[PDB]
Image (cartoon, rainbow, N blue to C red):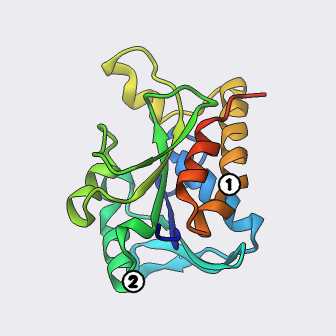
Amino acid sequence: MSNISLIVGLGNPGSEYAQTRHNAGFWFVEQLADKYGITLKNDPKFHGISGRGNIEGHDVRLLLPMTYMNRSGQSVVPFSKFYQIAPEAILIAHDELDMNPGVIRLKTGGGHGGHNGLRDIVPHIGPNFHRLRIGIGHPGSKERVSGHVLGKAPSNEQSLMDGAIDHALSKVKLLVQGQVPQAMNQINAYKPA
């Protein structure tokens, strides 16, 4: 398998969305960046904030679109095309409504599952990139979905999510080194301690 060479976190720009559940992807990539000392800088050419550096012996790019969530493809697509990165070398971290806080899964392929950031990406690069689905819970009804993803989690649910993100972070070495089945097994087995 392809090594993962581009890791994307999905979310919305600005301090009012930084702590919301819909920025789970940003939390993961920001924390990865600082773990490895990768600096994320403004990258207006690609409508995002990006960085590059060594993670566990491999040269990896990191991207946070600054397009707003529903327009994420306007950053991910031209960036991946410019650097000639195939979908199979891409990991996209995002909030997943269909999984509870503290649940996290790595998935390869499939569609957007209703996720409005992935909806903007699958059409243009196809589906065969990897996803880190960070569970944020489902509020109860189709009506409350928007206020839930656009809201800040209470501290109990947030700890659960952070625990899950910390675990995936510890598996990034397998991902960048091409070890995706092993990483999938090991990420997908997580349960809160």
Above or below residue 99? Residue 67 is: below
For badge 1, the amino acid type reads Lys
| Residue appearing at x 63%, y 35% in the figure | 189
Q: Which percent across, then down, holds residue 71? A: 31, 58
Q: Which residue is tagged 2? A: 45
Task: Quadrant for the C terminus, please.
Answer: top right
Answer left or right for 23 relative to 191: left
Q: Is residue 93 left or right of residue 124?
A: right
Q: Residue at x 68, y 67 (%)?
A: 33
Instruction: Say above or below: 23 vs 163.
Output: below
Q: Residue 31: give x, y in percent of width and height.
A: 69, 58
Residue linked to disc 1: 171
**Amino acid at pointer 2:** Lys
Q: Which residue is painted at 59% across and 43% down in the image?
A: 185
Residue 17 in sight from this viewpoint: no
Tell me which numbered mark, 1 or 2, is placed earlier along the sequence.
2
Q: Residue at x 40, y 85 (%)?
A: 83
Residue extending farthest top: 140
Whole-percent x, y for residue 183 in the image: 60, 52
Foreground residue among 12 and 14: 12
Q: Is residue 164 above or below residue 92?
A: above
